[PDB]
Structure formats: structure tokens, C-alpha cells
Image (cartoon, coloured by chain):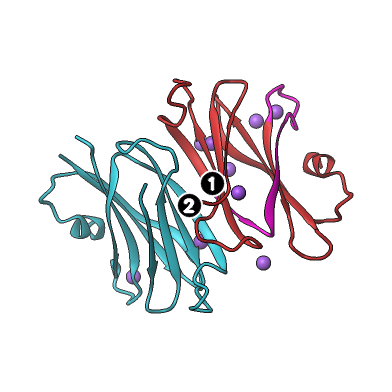
Chain colours: A red, B cyan
């Protein structure tokens, strides 16, 4: 099994993030799947929506931070290139009970010392 | 959890997966398309993917030309945990990528899913 992480949002919704099965470490895809989380004992029983995105590198971090000021965290998936420069890219998603899952922003080709969060707000 | 890889005669590669950790009876599946440009590395060149709901468990995959352009579409057939079939079809090509072709649902087990997907 490859990369898999499950997070519970403040609303009680549950999100999973996976890299594509059978893919190389250096490049491929990942998906984000949102669930209602209505029963925390069976958090993945009620699927809502999902997206598949390319990754130029490996997932390096998952962050839950409010980017748009609505008080709820967006999900940020930070990806680090296998290149010697370790260039960063990231996708942000809104995920909430009212709207479900949507893309918020995407950045790529960032130097390792760049402010990814500020870039995603830009 | 369902996982299957198919390779088209063009060389394109597709994988179909049920969502990890989900119930057998309900959840999601994803379809991922790769170029397969180097056939020894089928999953080295990702193109595009989609995540869909499944009302049931994946029964089988088919590759068949649904619109008569001589390229195969991908069909994902789903069986309810209860008896009904549903199915989603997708176009796949190097030129365009991955797109929805059609969707059918509430079919009897004996019905022709492929003819249903072809029929306006
Ligand atoms: K949405
Ligand atoms: K497309
Ligand atoms: Na891992
Ligand atoms: Na690339
Ligand atoms: Na927010
Ligand atoms: Na929003
Ligand atoms: Na919508
Ligand atoms: Na969207
Ligand atoms: Na066709």
C-alpha cells in the first residue's frame, strides 16, 4: 500500500488523501475524497465527492488552514519535487458541509523557501 | 477493495479502484488514465483521473467502442448490494484525455448494459 492519510475536519466531515496505486514515488497523481463523517465509528461510510490531481513529486505535508476567511480550514496538499532543487507545489481545496469539495487554488514551481500559504492566498 | 489495470491497444493504461477503507456496499471509485508511452512502465505518465460515486460494488470493467469511432470507451459496471445494475462509460484518448460518455442506472440483472449506454 502507498500513501494514505485520513483527517477529520472541524465540521465532523472526513477527508482522505491517497497517492495513486502502483505509481512511482517521484511522480504521478493523488486523490482527495470527502465523506460526511456522520458516524465517527465508521467515518468512511458516506462518500460525498472526490478529485484526482497530478503530483510533481511526493506529498510532503497536509495542512488544515483557513485561507479564505470563512473560519473553516481549507485542505492544503504540499508536494515536493524529486529534483535537486526540491521545488514545491501545492493544491488547496475547500471542503465544508454547505458546498462539499471544490478546488480553491494551485501553485507550482516554488523555491523551497517560498511562503506556500501566502502563495495559495494570492 | 477493487483494483484493476487495463491496457488499451493504443498503449494507454487505465486503473480503476474502489475507495480505500469504504464499505463493500457503497462508496466511490476512481478512474486514472496514463499514457503508457513506455509499456514497461505503465503507470509512469499520469494524464487525468475522476472520482465517482458507486451505488454498490464494481462488478466488472469493459473496453468497447460505444460511439463507432473505432476507439474503445471504458465501462464500469456496478452491482447493488441488495437486484439492479448501473454503469458509467468514459472516453479515453491521447488527444483529449478522460471524459464522461454516459451513465445508466436501475437496470435489471438480465438487461444489456452496453446497449443501454449506446441508446439515447
Ligand atoms: K462541490
Ligand atoms: K479531458
Ligand atoms: Na507511505
Ligand atoms: Na512531470
Ligand atoms: Na476557509
Ligand atoms: Na468556500
Ligand atoms: Na456542486
Ligand atoms: Na470545482
Ligand atoms: Na469509441
Which residue sits furthest left?
B110
Q: Are marks 2 and 1 on the same chain?
A: no
Work out whether B73 lies above or below A113: below
Image location (x, y in percent) of residue B50: 48, 52
From the viewer's perspective, is A14 left or right of A83?
left
Quadrant position of residue A62: top right
Quick check: is A13 in the magenta stretch?
A: no
A90 or B100: nearer the viewer: A90
Ligand 8 neighbours mark 1 (CB distance < 8 Å): yes
From the viewer's perspective, is B36 left or right of B55?
right
**Looking at the image, which residue is at 48% across and 26% down?**
A36
From the viewer's perspective, is A70 left or right of A1?
right
Q: Is residue B74 visible?
A: yes
Q: Is residue A108 visible?
A: no
**Looking at the image, which residue is at 48% across and 21% down?**
A40
Image location (x, y in percent) of residue A106: 71, 49
Q: How many marks?
A: 2
Work out whether A68 lies above or below A113: above
Residue under pointer 1: A51
Q: Using a 10 Å C-alpha cutoff, classify the residue at mark 2 as few (fewer than 14 neighbours), some (14 to 19) or many (20 or more).
A: some
Q: Which residues are magenta?
A: A52-73
Which residue sits furthest right?
A113
Q: Chain of mark 2?
A: B
Ligand 9 is found in the corner quadrant, namely bottom left
Q: Chain of mark 1?
A: A
Distance of label 2 from label 1 (alpha carbons): 6 Å
Quick check: is A53 in the magenta stretch?
A: yes
Image location (x, y in percent) of residue A30: 58, 51
Residue under pointer 2: B50
> Which numbered dot is residue B45?
none
Q: Using a 10 Å C-alpha cutoff, classify the residue at mark 1 as few (fewer than 14 neighbours), some (14 to 19) or many (20 or more).
A: some
**Looking at the image, which residue is at 54% across and 26% down?**
A13
Amino acid at each position: 500500500d502507498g500513501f494514505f492519510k485520513q483527517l477529520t475536519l472541524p465540521s465532523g466531515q472526513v477527508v482522505t488523501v491517497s497517492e495513486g496505486r502502483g505509481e512511482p514515488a517521484s511522480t504521478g497523481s493523488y486523490d482527495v475524497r470527502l465523506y460526511s463523517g456522520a458516524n465517527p465509528q465508521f467515518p468512511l461510510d458516506q462518500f460525498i465527492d472526490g478529485k484526482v490531481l497530478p503530483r510533481d513529486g511526493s506529498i510532503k505535508e497536509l495542512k488544515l488552514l483557513d485561507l479564505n476567511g470563512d473560519k473553516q480550514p481549507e485542505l492544503i496538499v504540499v508536494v515536493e519535487s524529486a529534483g535537486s532543487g526540491s521545488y514545491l507545489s501545492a493544491d488547496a481545496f475547500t471542503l465544508n458541509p454547505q458546498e462539499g469539495l471544490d478546488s480553491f487554488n494551485h501553485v507550482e514551481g516554488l523555491a523551497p523557501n517560498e511562503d506556500v500559504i501566502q502563495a495559495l492566498k494570492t
